[PDB]
Amino acid sequence: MKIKDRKHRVIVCSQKSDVDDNGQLLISRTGSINGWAAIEPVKAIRFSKDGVSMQKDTFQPTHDITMNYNPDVNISVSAWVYEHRLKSPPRWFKVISVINVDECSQFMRLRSRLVESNDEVEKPVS
Amino acid sequence: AFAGEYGITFEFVSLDISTEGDTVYIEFRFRQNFDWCEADRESDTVIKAGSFSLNL
Image 1: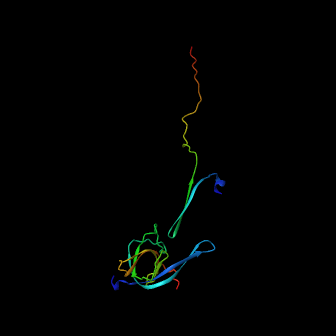
Image 2: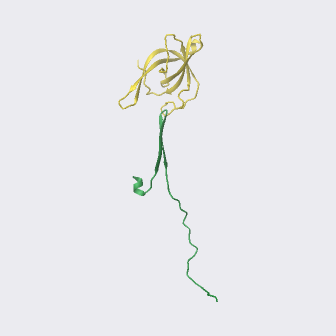
Image 3: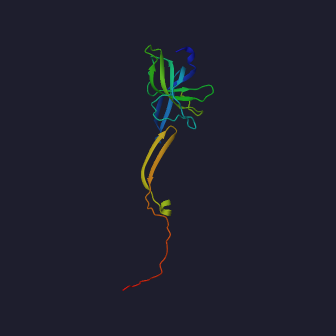
């Protein structure tokens, strides 16, 4: 990878969840990593009236995200990714799996599923 | 309410639920039982006569 590619600025978050009194499930997401990243699409998307992605088979990714490898980090199931851009609305990615560019251990590539993109998106807990 | 009002009743069969992104698909199934009849035909004639020849 070249330096210039990483156009995008992203925030990697962790998920903590619990149960309301009504029984519905609550989510809150905590920022943990900051840095530039490079993003590539892999699959088409269909947006509902407010941009929440609609697709069965949640396990298949849509976007590829690459950033600097970090030996002191342990990505896991509960990961997320957040991105706020100049004009276009924010977006939440859900992280599926992980892969080193090679065992050279220089860059960590994530496989992600797009979820939302609209003005009302909740911003990550600082 | 409607069935009591007019006299038409249904049979429940099953209920199934599933979700898809923003939308939730609630799916019902029903069944009707009824007789069937043919259209209203029209006669050919009416009867008034008698010959009764009464041969040998």
